[PDB]
Image (cartoon, coloured by chain):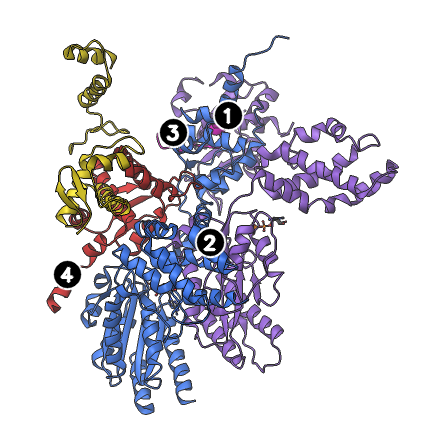
Amino acid sequence: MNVTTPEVAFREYQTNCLASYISADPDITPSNLILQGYSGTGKTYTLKKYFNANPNLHAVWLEPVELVSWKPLLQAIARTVQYKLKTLYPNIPTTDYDPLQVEEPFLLVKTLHNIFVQYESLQEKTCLFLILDGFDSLQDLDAALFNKYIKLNELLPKDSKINIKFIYTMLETSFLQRYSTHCIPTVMFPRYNVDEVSTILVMSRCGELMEDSCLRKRIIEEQITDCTDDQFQNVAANFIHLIVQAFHSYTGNDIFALNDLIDFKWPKYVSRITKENIFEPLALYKSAIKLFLSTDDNLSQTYDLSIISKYLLIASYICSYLEPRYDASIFSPRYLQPSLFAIERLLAIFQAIFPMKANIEVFQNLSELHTLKLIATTMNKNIDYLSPKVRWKVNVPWEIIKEISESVHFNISDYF
Amino acid sequence: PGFGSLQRRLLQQLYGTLPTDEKIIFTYLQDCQQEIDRIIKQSIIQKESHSVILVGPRQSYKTYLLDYELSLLQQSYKEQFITIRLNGFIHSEQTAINGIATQLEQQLQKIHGLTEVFEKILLLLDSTTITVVFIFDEIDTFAGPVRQTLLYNLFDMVEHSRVPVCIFGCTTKLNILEYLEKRVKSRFSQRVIYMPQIQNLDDMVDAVRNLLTVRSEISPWVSQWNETLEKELSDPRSNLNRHIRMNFETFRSLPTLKNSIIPLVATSKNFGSLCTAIKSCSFLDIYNKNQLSNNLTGRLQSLSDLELAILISAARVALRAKDGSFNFNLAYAEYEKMIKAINSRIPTVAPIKLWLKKDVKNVWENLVQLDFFTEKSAVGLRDNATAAFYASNYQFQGTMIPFDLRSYQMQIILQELRRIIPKSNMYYSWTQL
Amino acid sequence: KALNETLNSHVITFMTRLSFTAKLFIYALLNLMKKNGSQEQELGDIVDEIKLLIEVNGSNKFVMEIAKTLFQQGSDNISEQLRIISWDFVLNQLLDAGILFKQTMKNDRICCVKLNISVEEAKRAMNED
Amino acid sequence: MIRLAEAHAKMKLKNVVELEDVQEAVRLIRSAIKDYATDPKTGKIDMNLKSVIQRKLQEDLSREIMNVLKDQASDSMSFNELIKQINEHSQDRVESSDIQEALSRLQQEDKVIVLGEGVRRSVR
Ligand SMILES: Nc1ncnc2c1ncn2[C@@H]1O[C@H](COP(=O)(O)OP(=O)(O)OP(=O)(O)O)[C@@H](O)[C@H]1O
Ligand SMILES: Nc1ncnc2c1ncn2[C@@H]1O[C@H](COP(=O)(O)OP(=O)(O)OP(=O)(O)O)[C@@H](O)[C@H]1O
């Protein structure tokens, strides 16, 4: 019955809680168990880490992340349970049931019952820990779904030698609070503190970066003579602390974004390394400064457009943010979303502001803008521009309209 | 080494899968337990036909009594009852019939080693002869506006079956007699039983005494365990007694307290450690705070400086708004304005960063996921699969409009922020308008 | 005896046997129904109306202990909560029993809550406490 | 508040202004404005000015009176002794009428014995 416990840092309470509720005897484990925590909390890490120290526990792993809807989730349970039972106890003569025949939860219960009856010849009652990771991460999800897996194993015959012991992992708190009356054993994961995130990153992603090809070049290029592994470890470790203290207020406390920033900035930081840069990381900071001054998560005269298109996009912004009351006076709410307008207004304002009549090039540029999605419409499928019901709005921010006005020498700044 | 025997015995009694000879019935339940048992024995032993619905909230021990009665009767009448189980959540209005058909055959196999379906079931029973037992959880689901043909047939079979027939229903609604249609309501025997609620602290103390005591000499420390349990339940100033009183005052579902206690017994490594833990009773506080760790305060304590400042600025805009709505542009404008004010109140020297609008996007994304914000009319998690289908078919405007102009509403009002945010925070002075 | 069990309703006695937090919830909801003349109250109203009802009597000594129970569960290691202990538990339990009606909205403050039972029997249940 | 504090002592014809003058002055302002009957977030007037919370307070007070009576090593105690032991021992002093009400309820339920005004005695 006794289960050994791995020493997972910053999850000691939860590791003790998983030492509870999980044991060989199915009479000492509950029918359902939920571990909850937002993304980047270590639940998928900790659960696997605990199962990897006690092989005798028969665990089945599935991920609703891959399994788009509930039908794959049902079918995978039967498939993987059957395969695992064959892998563990092969000598018993059994007959296969097609996992694609599981079209309903009742059929899942039927198939599980049949499989356990086929294994009835077992001497001892044993557990079967079916594991689902990120139940609420399922994309085709509704509230009523989870009760079906809460109240499942009581429809199984309790005489069976194999007992299913569900384990769930969840992200949101608004999902748990609809099921608090069931008193299901719950283990909680809070977001890590900064002191925890920094140490987790140092422990995890240090050696992997320490021996990358980029340094394999630079060490020989700089002809480092007295280098040892400890110096490598310290130099690599300083990078994580610098990035964390630089971008903590930007990323927050998430491991993933910090890892991505480290991945992007590590070759560039390594590039600045010289003979005099190591053993004085302060100089390394004082030379790679511009890496720590911009996030560099950006994917890369920003718009090069025809003059007619530029003035059309000026007039459309005027239409989208000027109240209709002023069209008869001025020409004769920035923070809010743009209002809708009609093409009749756009053409008139464009004619009134261009330094043109109705040649086809104007309409061609307008349709180009729509195809460029610099101007939006009130529809999603089967675009029917010529239908009178469609209305138009601007999909471009002010910061670009200002530059367009500068490039065409226009004075939108004086109309508001 | 021997401590493990008693430590496992305690857990095995706690989970409740005890042998019928060792099982426990709490005192306040016994009246309804006997009311149920009399009907069950009348239907099985004396071949009566009856239909009963049990009432009470979830985790009210409602099905535990039925399980105990069936486990008792299996000892003396093993060959004289057939049990049919149906659950409202798993079985739809279609899959119930197939479940009945499969379970009947499954029971018959180990026994021997809808206009006509029910009649043919009765004829097969007659030709093979045994009392048929029906158990329903979530009666209200079967008693919805969807046609109630299943229960309509089951309650009709009560006074017409040539084979003894018994039906038990389980649900938490109190308006069951209005859930059932007038046609079905007429046919039902209407012997409604409401589960007895814990209504005194003496009831809960006695329930704990019944649940945690050991009635046999499994371990030499059983006598010490029972004595210590009674001592802690006796002294009003015991930490365990205080926690039990708090539980009774707050919520009166006993299985919640059971599940709270389970980790304390499970974690115990030695008898001395068990005694010290149960006397101090401090680990329930740790359990309770972990139950609260992902609440609003717990999430708010984990945010960064810039995240907190942007949250405060968003809250200020929500407060000033007539409807509480706000967007990214207004939030960044207020963030810039407050940074300018903070810089201005710092005197200039004779001869704090405003983060770029692009960098603030990650902070906004972080806060939208942690549910501090919410979209203007976000329904959130839909209730049923059909609603999810119609929701996934439709395309909401809030998912199409730019990142800078999506309308949001606030979950933590500025007053709550001023309650929670430490005064040592630099941005605390802006928790007021 | 058969006629009595057909006529009598368990609603009132079940309410009188509810835990303290549920009775406090119903009392605060009735108080808001009186002070506003409305049928439904947002959780944004009720969560702080309970705080108001605790604070009005706050001059009493045992109000400190009941506040410690409701907002920190009687432990020093737990900080202030924006909900009373088991707010979710009792909120669901009243919905589970059919006493209460709640409208779907993923915002924990603008969500509206309405009684399903009649007002007079709720008043009677509150009077018997 | 200060002007009313001086005005009260002038009625008292006393050379100084003291706590009773200040507290009465504070109360008079409270009663004049009708503060406690006014909602603190809407400014509306409560036209009603025993709640369940009051019922709980009296329940716990009676139970604590029983606990103090049965826990002390004396079969009987005076109400002043009880006040010194509990009411004035911790937190600001509460009005003794509530203690008297609780012990009177217990006596009516025959849980405590009140032989006289000066003494309170345990159960028979
Ligand atoms: N205590 C820890 N020590 C070291 N690394 C940890 C620890 N906890 C979490 N991690 C790291 O967290 C990373 C992310 O995995 P994690 O288990 O946190 O995901 P998750 O929260 O389950 O994700 P999702 O919701 O997307 O499924 C892992 O790669 C792991 O290295
Ligand atoms: N076979 C069993 N062995 C031990 N305990 C059981 C068993 N079945 C139920 N219980 C106990 O029942 C308690 C919860 O009540 P129960 O299971 O009777 O309600 P329910 O049928 O789920 O209720 P409802 O249908 O009203 O939601 C738990 O504490 C659990 O320990």
Q: Which chain is mark 4 on?
A: C
Count numbered badges in the picture: 4
Q: Marks 4 and 2: same chain?
A: no
Chain shown yellow: that is D
| Vertical placement of residue A398 versus B301, above or below | above
> Which one is earlier in the sequence, the residue at label 3 or at label 1?
3
Task: Tell me the crowding category of disc 3: few under 14, some 14 to 19, or many 20 or more residues within 10 angstroms, Cα based.
Answer: some
Is the CB of the residue bearing disc 4 within 8 angstroms of ligand 2?
Answer: no
Chain shown red: that is C
Secondary structure state at the residue bearing disc 4:
loop
Task: Name the quadrant of the N terminus of chain A.
Answer: bottom right
| Residue A194 on the magenta segment | no
The residue where tag 3 is placed is B319
The residue where tag 4 is placed is C8
> Which one is earlier in the sequence, the residue at label 1 or at label 2?
2
Check disc 1 and give the amino acid type: Met
Check disc 2 and give the amino acid type: Thr
Describe residue B82's horizontal placement relative to residue A166 as left or right: left
Circles 3 and 2: CB atoms closer than 8 Å: no
The residue where tag 2 is placed is B276
Q: Quadrant of residue B63?
A: bottom left
Secondary structure state at the residue bearing disc 2:
helix
Residue range in magenta is B321-335
Residue appearing at x 50%, y 25% in the figure: B426
Secondary structure state at the residue bearing disc 1:
helix
Q: Marks 1 and 2: same chain?
A: yes
Describe residue A269's horizontal placement relative to residue A86 as left or right: right
**Label 3 to label 4, Cα distance in Å?**
49 Å
Q: Which mark is residue B426?
A: 1
Secondary structure state at the residue bearing disc 3:
helix
Which of pointers 1 and 2 indicates the residue nearer the eye? 2
